[PDB]
Image 1 (cartoon, helix red, strand yellow):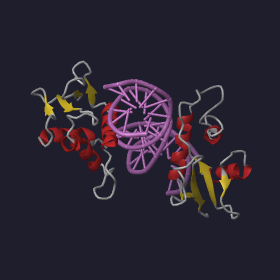
Image 2 (cartoon, rainbow over the protein chains, first blue to last red):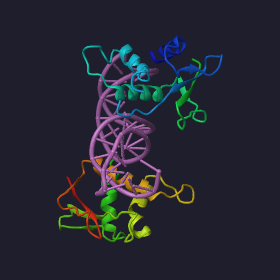
Image 3 (cartoon, rainbow over the protein chains, first blue to last red):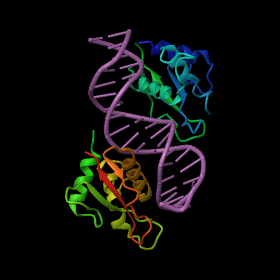
Image 4 (cartoon, protein in one colour):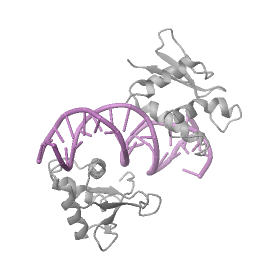
Length: 107
Length: 109
DNA sequence: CAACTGAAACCGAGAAACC
DNA sequence: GGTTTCTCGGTTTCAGTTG
């Protein structure tokens, strides 16, 4: 299970706008969830790229780039994981710069 | 899995929907009315019934709770038919240009 | 942006595929 | 036995058109 530490590292790194902590206990955090158009095209997908690079699912100069399945893989991994739970009453999919709110369960 | 095909077959066989009829004996091709809501020949009840029925069958719409939106129901069903491999539209036989327009669909086995 | 459209992006729920 | 991807069967948004 490499998702937990990986995500925490990426949030602490802060190389991703919109990706912030929600409390000084480092337990709840936002993640930008915007709908792609035909292309907000690369800066947002960086996470979805990073993950695909980390788990070796995308190798630069070997595979064809494909942001939709990167975002989908991360979505399915975050939904099916047990270390993360969506605070649905806190998510905000109905604004400009929308996001989803997640709590990190202790383990 | 696979609810749309059987559901539409039962709807066609139900006779509850005027204009929703088989067009051959083998039950392989069928006609489905396709009236534009903005026109005057449009009966709200009868012409939205099938779309509403699909939006009820899948729990997307709930009576008394949600607010009715016939155009969403229409778009939902149309995109669904387009996506599925069980249904193929026969564009040269659909007549979306008469006073009572309709689409025609063939059921692939 | 009223109703409508095709195409693409999107989604959850199992079922594999990994680990 | 423990996580992450893949598949399937539709659904919803995007960028326009009046189908």
